[PDB]
Amino acid sequence: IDTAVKTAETGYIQRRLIKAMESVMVNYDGTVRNSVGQLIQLRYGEDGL
DNA sequence: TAACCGCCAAGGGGATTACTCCCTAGTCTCCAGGCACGTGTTTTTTTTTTTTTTTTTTTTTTTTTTTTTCCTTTTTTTTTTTTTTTT
Image 1 (cartoon, rainbow, N blue to C red):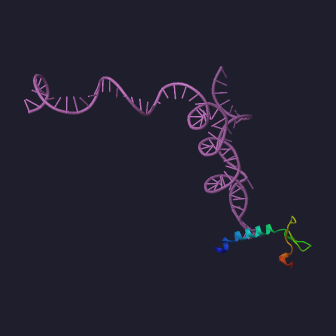
Image 2: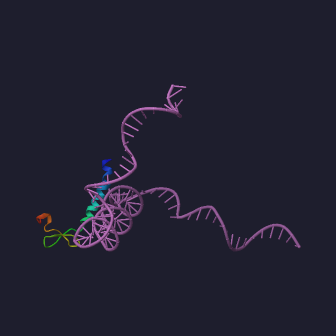
C-alpha cells in the first residue's frame, strides 16, 4: 500500500521540481542565472565547484 | 337628660382720643445688571475604506510497454411511389 500510494505524488513533485529549475544556468562568469538572466548565485554552491 | 330660657353677676379687652415718630412717597442723579443679538462646539448623520469570513472556481492527480473487444447511431417524422376502388 505504501509503495502504491505515495508514488503518484512523488512523480508529481519530481515533475514540478524539474519544471521550476529547468533553466537555472551556470554562465561563463561563474555566476548562476535563470532563463531571464536574473542572478541567483554568484558562485555555484557558494564556492564555484 | 341637658338644650334652652331667664335672671343675675362679674370682668376683660376692643373702641376711642391724643401724642409722637419714623418709615416710606416723592424727586433727582449715577451707574450697572437685565436683556437683545450673535454664535458655538458637541451631536448626530453619512460616507469610506477596510476586515473577515464564506463561497465559488479551477486545476491537479509517476512514467514506459504489451494483448483483446465494442463501436465507429437511431428512432421519428415527412415524403414519394405503388396499389386498389369507383364511375
